[PDB]
Every structure is written in structure tokens, then in C-alpha cells.
Image (cartoon, coloured by chain):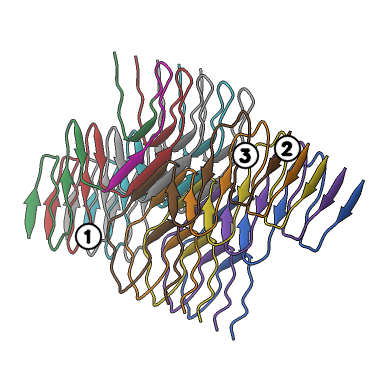
Chain colours: A cyan, C red, D green, F brown, G orange, H yellow, I purple, J blue
Amino acid sequence: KKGVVHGVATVAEKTKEQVTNVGGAVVTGVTAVAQKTVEGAGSIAAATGFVKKDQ
Amino acid sequence: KKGVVHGVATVAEKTKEQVTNVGGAVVTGVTAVAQKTVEGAGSIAAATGFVKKDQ
Amino acid sequence: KKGVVHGVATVAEKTKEQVTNVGGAVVTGVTAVAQKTVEGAGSIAAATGFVKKDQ
Amino acid sequence: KKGVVHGVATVAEKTKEQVTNVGGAVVTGVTAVAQKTVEGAGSIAAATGFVKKDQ
Amino acid sequence: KKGVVHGVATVAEKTKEQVTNVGGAVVTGVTAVAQKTVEGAGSIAAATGFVKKDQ
Amino acid sequence: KKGVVHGVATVAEKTKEQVTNVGGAVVTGVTAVAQKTVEGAGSIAAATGFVKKDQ
Amino acid sequence: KKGVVHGVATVAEKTKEQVTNVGGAVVTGVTAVAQKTVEGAGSIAAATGFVKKDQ
Amino acid sequence: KKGVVHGVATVAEKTKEQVTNVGGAVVTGVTAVAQKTVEGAGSIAAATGFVKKDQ
Amino acid sequence: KKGVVHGVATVAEKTKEQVTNVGGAVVTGVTAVAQKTVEGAGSIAAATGFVKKDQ
Amino acid sequence: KKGVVHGVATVAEKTKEQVTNVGGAVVTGVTAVAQKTVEGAGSIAAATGFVKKDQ
């Protein structure tokens, strides 16, 4: 076989899960957050996949 | 087989799940948030997939 | 087989779920949010798939 | 088989769900939000798939 | 076989999970956060995959 | 002060919430159930406060 | 002060929450269930407060 | 002070939370269940407070 | 002071939390369950407070 | 002071937490279970407080 990509690719066979991202956010997984009190200014309480590039 | 992509591709066979994103947000997964009190200015309480690029 | 894409594609066979996004938001998954009080100015309380690019 | 796309495509066979988006928003999944009080100016309380690009 | 990529690629066969990211965040895994009180200004309470590049 | 009860009482001062039950069911709290498929004969899918005394 | 009870009482002062139960079920708390598939005969999927006394 | 109870009592002062139960179930706490697939006959998947006295 | 109980009592002062139970189940605490697949016949997957007295 | 109990009592002063149980189950503590696959017939996967007296 032959393949040429510029990116971003994701090429496969017999594949149970696939995610391609440029951005941006993708949530595909099981996630449970239980929480009782959030205070403070300002605290990232429960972050799973996170990116902060403030300018 | 032969394939040429510019991106972003996601090419496969026999594949249970697929996500392609440029952006942007995609939520495809099970997610449960239970929460009782959020305060503060300003706190990211429960973030799963998150991207902040303020300018 | 042969395939040429510019992107964004999502090409497959025998595939249970598919999402293609450029944008933008796509919500296809099970999601439960239970919440009792949100305060503060301004706090992202419960974000699952999120993108903030304010200019 | 043969396929050439410009994007955004989503090509498949035997496929239970499909979403193609350029935009924009698509909601196809089960979603339950229960909520008791939202205050503050201005707090994104419960966001599932979200994109904010204010200029 | 032959392959030439510019990156970022992810090329495979017989592959159970795949993630390609440029960004950005991708959450595909099981995650449980249980939490009782978050205070302080400002403390990253529970971060799993995290990136902070404030300027 | 003086108090004599037979039960069931609930006596208080300065009290934000109160529930008295003999029975029976009382639901006063925030509750979010999101659900996609229930099968089987017969499975209690999502029970929060539950009592089964079949004879 | 003086108090005589037969039960079940709940006597207090300056008290934020109170529950008295004989039964029976009382749900006063925040609860989020997100769920995607329930099968089997018969499986208690997600039980929070539960009592089964079948005869 | 003086107190005589038969039970079940719960007597206090300056008390943030109170639960009295004879039964029966009481759910007053924050709870998040996220779940993707339940099978089998019959499996208690996610039980928090649970009592099974089948006869 | 003087106190005579038959049980079950719970007598206190200046007390943040109280639970009295005869039964039965009481859930007052923060709880997060995230789960992806439950199979088998029949397996207690995730049990927090649990009592099984089948006859 | 004077006290006579039959049991089960729990008598105190200046006390942050209290639990009295006859039964039965009480869950008052923070608990996080994250889990990916449960199989087998039948295996107690993750048990925190547990009692099995099958007859």
C-alpha cells in the first residue's frame, strides 16, 4: 500500500476508536465528576483535558 | 490501496467510533457531572475537554 | 481501493458512529448535569467540550 | 472502490450514526440538565458542546 | 509498503485506540473525580492532562 | 424549653431544609438522569432513593 | 431544656438540613446519572440509596 | 439538660446536617455516576448505599 | 446533664454531621463512579456501602 | 454527668462527624471509583465497605 499525508491524518484498519483533533476539544470517554463546593478566584477545580494559552 | 490526504483526514475500516475535528468541540462520550455549589470569580469548576486562547 | 481527500474527511466501513466537524459544536453523547447553585462572575461551572477564543 | 472529496465528507457503510457539520451546532445525543439556581454576570453554567469566538 | 508524512500522522493496522492531537485537548479515557471542597486563589485542584502557557 | 414527641417529629430553629416522611417518598433535591437504552426483565436501571418490599 | 421522645425524632437548633424517615425513601441531594446501555435480567445498574426486602 | 429517648433519636445543637432513618433509604449527598454499558444477569453495577435481604 | 437511651441514639453538641440508621441505607457523602463496561453474572462492580443477607 | 445506654448509642460533644448504624449501610465519605472493564462470574471488583452473609 501507499500513503502520503500532510497532517494531521489518522489512518488505520480494524480499529475500535479514532480521534483526530486540531483545535479545540474532543471528549469521547467516560467521565464522572461529583463535587460539593468550589470557591476561590480563580481555581481550576477538576480539569481532565485542558489547555490555557491566554495572551 | 492508495491514499493521499491534505489533512485532517481519518481513514479506516471496521471501526466502531470516529471523530474528526477542526475547531471547535465534539462531545460523543458518556459524561456525568453532579455539583452542589460554584462560587468565585472566576473558577473553571469541572472542565472535561477545554481550550482557552483569549487574546 | 483509492482515495484522495482535501480534508476534513472521515472515510470508513462497518462503523458504528461518525462525527465530522469544522466549527462549531457537535454533541452526540449521553450527558447528565445536575446542579444546585452557580454564582460568581464569571465561572465556567460544568463544561464538557469547550473552546473559547475571544479577541 | 474510488473516492475523491474536497471536504467535509463522511463516507461509510453499515453505519449506525453520522454527523457532518460546518458551522454551527448539531445535537443528536441524550442530554439531561437539572439545575436549581444560576447567578453571576456572566457564567457559563452547564455547557456541553460550546464554541465562543467573540471579536 | 511506502509512507511519507509531514506530521502529525498516526498510521497503523489492527489498532484498538488512536488519538491525534494538535492543540488542544482530547479526553478518551475513563475518569472519576470525587471532591468535597476547593478553596484558595488559585489552586489547580485535580488536573489530569493539563497545559498552561499564559503570556 | 420543653418538648415531648411520639414520633416522627422534626423540631428545629434557623433551619434551611426539612423533610419528614412516613411512607412513602419525598423528592426535594436536584436530580438529572440522562439515559440512552434500558433493556432486560427486569433491571432497576437508575434508582436514587428506593425501597422494595414485595410480599 | 428537657426532651422526651418515642422515636423517631430529630431535634436541633441552627441546623442547615434535616431528614426524618420511616419507610420509605427521601432524596434531597444532588444526583447526576448519565448512562448509555442497560441490559441483563436483572441487574441493579446504578443504585444510590437502596433497600430490597423481597419475601 | 435532660433527655430520654426510645430510639431512634438524633439530638444536637449547631449542627449542619442531620439524617434519621429506619427503613429504607435516604440520599442527601452529591453523587455522580457515569456509565457506558451494563450487561450480565444480574450484576450490581454501581451501588453506593445498598441493602439486600431477599427471603 | 443526664441521658438515658434505648438505642439507637446519636446525641451531641456543636456537630457538623450526623447520621442515624437502622435498616437500610443512608448516603450523605460525595461519590463519583465512572465506568465503561460491566459484564458477568453476577459481579458486584463498584460497591461503596453494601450489605447482602440473602436467605 | 450521667448516662445509661442499651446500645447502640454514640454520645459526644464538640464533634465534627457522627455515624450510628445497625444494618445496613452508611456512606458519608469521599469516594472515587474509575473503572474500565469488569468481567467474570462473579467477582467483587471494587468494594469499599462490604458485608456478605448469604445463607
Q: Quadrant of the rendered structure where residue I36 is?
A: bottom left
Q: Is residue D27 above or below residue J43?
A: above
Say which element carries label 3: loop
Q: Which residue is mark 2?
A: F2
User: What span is in magenta?
Assistant: D30-43
Residue drawn at point x = 36 percent, y = 25 percent = C52
Residue drawn at point x = 60 percent, y = 64 percent = I23
Q: Are marks 2 and 3 on the same chain?
A: yes
Q: Amino acid at mark 3?
A: Val
Say which element carries label 2: strand
Q: Main secondary structure of the magenta part?
A: loop
**Closer to us: C19 or C1:** C19
Magenta residue check for A22: no
Residue drawn at point x = 56 percent, y = 73 percent = J44
**Closer to us: G12 or F5:** F5
Distance CA(mark 2)–CA(mark 3) = 11 Å
Q: Are marks 2 and 1 on the same chain?
A: no
Q: Which residue is mark 1?
A: C16
